[PDB]
Amino acid sequence: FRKMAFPSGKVEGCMVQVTCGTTTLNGLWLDDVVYCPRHVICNPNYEDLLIRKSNHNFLVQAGNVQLRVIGHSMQNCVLKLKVDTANPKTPKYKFVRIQPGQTFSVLACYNGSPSGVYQCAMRPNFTIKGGSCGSVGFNIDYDCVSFCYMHHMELPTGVHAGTDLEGNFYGPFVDRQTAQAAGTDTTITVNVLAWLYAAVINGDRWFLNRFTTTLNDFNLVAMKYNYEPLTQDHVDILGPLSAQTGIAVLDMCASLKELLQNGMNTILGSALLEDEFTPFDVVR
Amino acid sequence: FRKMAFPSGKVEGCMVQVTCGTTTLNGLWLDDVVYCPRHVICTSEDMLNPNYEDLLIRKSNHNFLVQAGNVQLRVIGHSMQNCVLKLKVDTANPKTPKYKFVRIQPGQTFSVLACYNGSPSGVYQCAMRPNFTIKGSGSCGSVGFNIDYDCVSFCYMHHMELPTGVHAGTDLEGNFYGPFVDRQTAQAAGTDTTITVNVLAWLYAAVGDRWFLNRFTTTLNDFNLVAMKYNYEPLTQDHVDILGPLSAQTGIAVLDMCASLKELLQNGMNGRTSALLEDEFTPFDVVR
């Protein structure tokens, strides 16, 4: 069972380079606006550093073409540079905010040049295990690109932190050089179950047993092994996989609890339990 | 350290749909030629004992329906080269990237753009397994590729699913990788082995981590005698030479890293970490 990223072509055509003084990073060019991390203009005072800036302080490059900046503005932690040319490659798109445990693709870029694409999950501690600042994360739904993430900073443990495209941070982080750390992370329980349903669909059934559990008894077992608590909405989202396979969610929870205590001695050719597929990803 | 796929845009603009009779799969549209698996001319029954010469001589250009998104492309010639069909169309693909065709060796990595009926669905990073199969994920005609300096090197086209769930296919000149054929025979992927040179390249990548090093070395022969007991591919002098650069930047001799690998296979990771020894990053990949 392979992790798959969305085809990145629609996003590739939007990546540009943004330079303010000696700082260069990636920007996202949609119609006649380029979006990028506001710290490109850098205990900072952003409203003051931006008032001191003029359009001529920004250099925007789309491949060979220099784009002329004709207005600048800030929205939370994202800088919005109005430019002289509308991106003729602008896809149908929306700005969305995702929740911990949801997945998306990141197009990693260096100085406006796309480098590679990978599938991510937003960890429960709101970080991502992933010159890349300004790279964006996204899902694609029938020609429409839903941008959900922009990369702002690396945390000392090596994970990544960023904002939605409206500039709102994911997690308790700020765009300053102060000391910050990811909280203790947790495993995304609903995604592990979705992945177990994927195993059954792929004909791997050895971890199934005759037992069922209670939502409360599993959650006491899940909290002990550092798993996110499972909710009734989690049971409802797993519904379609419980109908296709005939294994009820609390039946699958029984299986997971037994795996968390005895090991696999094996499941989709994996050793650990994979938690970066959502219920939606598995159906797809 | 993520397994990253190449940005897929340059290949997305080349994917089309090819239909012959009731069979539809993916094709690759480069200049005025569409490449697809020749078994597009087979009707499942034919797959048991297909005679491609006889099946193809009976087709005319208008039997092949080629669609590039909305536009139907007019086929004006056709030709078979080994196991790929080459359909000459009336229009050269305006989105053709700089490209070339290359045949790869087991252990080499590449990205696959998985497609259904001509429309890209997802992209993933791959290695050609030593048994010449792909542990990948209607997808016939999807292609594998590397991109170096805006040039797309096409190295794989998907043709067959094997009974164990893995995939077999050809280069873009239609020559199968491994002993597989585009016929529904009892054919199966032989026991697969770990790509040793890639594991070692990854260990060099690990080295600000060095908990797994030890004070031992090994001969090449002793390493291979041990590693083959874990179903690891034999390590050659070519492989030793390939890892030379990574051996320098880290200061760890290749056979010293081999000794570390021997101990990791003996011990495991003792709850530390991936909890797996990873073999789908090449020495070239690691440096990049």
Image (cartoon, coloured by chain):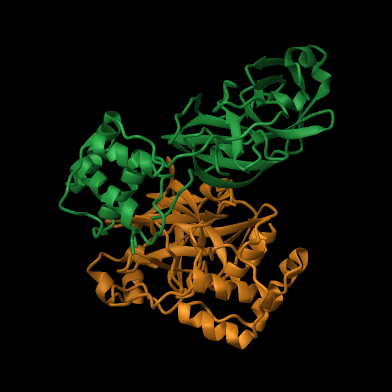
Chain colours: A green, B orange
State whether residue A221 appears in this view. yes
Question: Would residue A61 be found to the left or right of residue B135 on screen?
Answer: right
Camera-nearest residue between A28 and B183 = A28
Does residue B244 lie above or below B19 as drawn?
A: below
Where the C terminus of chain A falls, by quadrant?
A: top left
Q: Vertical placement of B19 versus B225: above or below?
A: above
The residue shown at (46%, 29%) is A98
Q: Please name the residue shown 49% across and 50% down the image.
A: B123
- Residue B270: image location, x then y, percent: 50, 62
Q: Quadrant of residue B187 in the image?
A: bottom left
The number of numbered badges drawn on the structure is: 0
Residue B196, visible in the rendered structure: no
Up the image or down, A269 lies above or below A90; here it is: below
Residue A246: x and y in percent read 16, 46
Q: Position of residue A229 (x, y in %)?
A: 35, 34
Residue closest to the eye, B228 or A112: B228
The N terminus of chain A lies in quadrant: bottom left
Classify residue A52 as left or right of residue A38.
right
Residue at image location 39% in from the left, 52% down from the top: A273
Image quadrant where residue A110 sits:
top right
Decide if residue B15 is on the left or right side of residue A167. Answer: left
